[PDB]
Amino acid sequence: SSAKRVFEKFDKNKDGKLSLDEFREVALAFSPYFTQEDIVKFFEEIDVDGNGELNADEFTSCIEKML
């Protein structure tokens, strides 16, 4: 599962969590077809802890949306 690997490359906050901002830069950068509504609906949907960022377990499910 290259979901953590891809996250490392995006860990722009070396925090172990991404913001819809990193996943939106991630989504707009590699998968530009991702509509901001699909990225935010899903990110808003995957960001389960509500910290406003993709956590590690959700990170893999954040990528499971593909990969």
Image (cartoon, grey):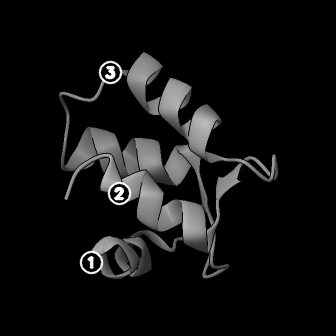
Q: Is residue 31 left or right of residue 23?
A: left
Q: Quick one: label 1, few (<14), some, or many (20+) residues within 10 Å?
A: few
Say which residue label 2 marks: 63
Q: Quadrant of residue 34?
A: top left
Separation (CA) of disc 3 from disc 2: 15 Å
Q: Nearer the viewer, mark 3 or mark 2?
A: 2
**Residue type, numbered disc 1:** Ser
- Residue 35's spot in the image, x, y percent? 32, 21
Q: Is residue 17 left or right of residue 42?
A: right
> Label for residue 1?
1
Q: Is residue 27 above or below residue 1?
A: above
Q: Nearer the viewer, mark 1 or mark 3?
A: 1
Question: Closer to the N terminus: mark 3 or mark 2?
Answer: 3
**Residue type, numbered disc 3:** Thr
Separation (CA) of disc 1 from disc 2: 9 Å
Q: Quadrant of residue 31?
A: top left
Q: Quick one: label 3, few (<14), some, or many (20+) residues within 10 Å?
A: few
Evaluate if marks 1 and 2 touch, with contact meaning CB atoms under 8 Å apart.
Answer: yes
* Element assignment for label 1: loop
- Residue 53's spot in the image, x, y percent? 67, 54
> Label for residue 35?
3
Q: Residue at x 60, y 35 (%)?
A: 45
Q: Quadrant of the C terminus?
A: bottom left
